[PDB]
Length: 165
Ligand SMILES: CCCn1nnc(NC(=O)c2ccco2)n1
Image (cartoon, rainbow, N blue to C red):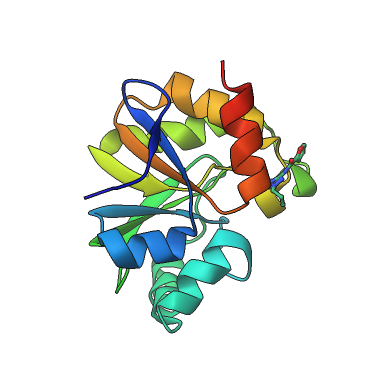
């Protein structure tokens, strides 16, 4: 199962890890992708997860969008986890760099409650432009299921742990 995580709360754990390497090692039931509404996995966590699937995640995602149209900011869809997990839960956190409502971050984390255990990144962090300290606080105050957070950046991981209330 998951190893080397620091316990933050009853149900939230955190580790300085590359979520792709973590997914290949654990092969969890659910890996969360930091998706956009179009499921265009170009960069950040999405670009890295997609590259690890040899673009199979993008091919599956384009078929999903062709059939269903875009997701909502704050929404999600369950697709295959390919070689990384049983399932990938593509969750759209607000992208502050695109002027999206930061208040939708709680709605985005509510998607995690439909899964008993997940390997996940901090939503809206990184290239999505939100403050990761705020993302972690919304995560702990919203998610009730078991969430194993992988934070790629060591310096950010240390700041998140040392400032956690
Ligand atoms: C790229 C280094 C790790 N990192 N990942 N997301 C962030 N972002 C921030 O620290 C930030 C954005 C708005 C306020 O603070 N840093």
